[PDB]
Image 1 (cartoon, helix red, strand yellow):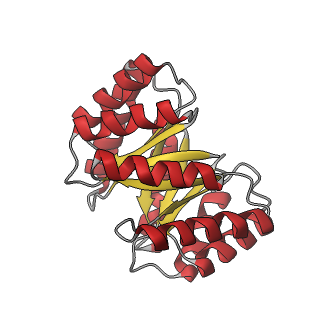
Image 2 (spheres, rainbow, N blue to C red):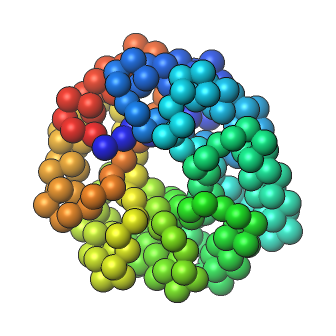
Image 3 (cartoon, rainbow, N blue to C red):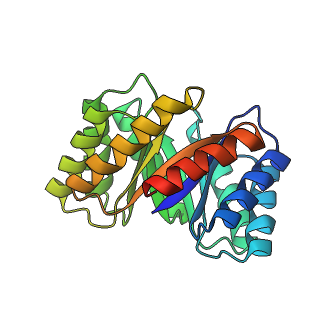
Amino acid sequence: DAICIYLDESATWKDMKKAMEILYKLGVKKIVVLFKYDEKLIKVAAKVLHDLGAEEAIIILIFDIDDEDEFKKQVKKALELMKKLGVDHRIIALRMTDEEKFKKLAKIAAELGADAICIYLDESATWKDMKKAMEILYKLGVKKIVVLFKYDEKLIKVAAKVLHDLGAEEAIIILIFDIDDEDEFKKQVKKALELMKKLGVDHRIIALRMTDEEKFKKLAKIAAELGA
């Protein structure tokens, strides 16, 4: 499928731009980018994607706001900027935590015009939290459910079963991998893709942390040759 660039929070916008050109060069049509809401990062992603001309790209914005009106405030500002910039596919990522908190926040993002909603599970999340989050998004009637987590075989099988149970045909799984150990990275990515294809996950994205240009190019090559 596609490849998502995850910005290392120690990465800069020049790091981001270089990761995008590398994927373009490798022949990746769907270049997805993932970061915590950042006005400057949104503007750079939009210009680079326009320069490359891959209007089949996606910006995924991570929000982590306690406050409910600060959330609406920021999600509105984010979506309107992305609208100015002609970003056709904008997704708002929400971490799970409180069940009621998750529902009101997803509702707010859906109201403001978020194209899809993404479930971002942090390492404090269980598979039971994931299932509940997915059921809440389905109940709300959101079009495309997206789930984003660190590579985990249980979470993959659970996610695949819940989507099949809800009938969520448009849903997407995005997996984040550790990168320091390149051998393990190759093994885990290989395994992830095989297992997701056995379970009929049709829309799966491999996410790569952007660190060093030399490192990123290695990982992206590996992921592409394996089938991402």
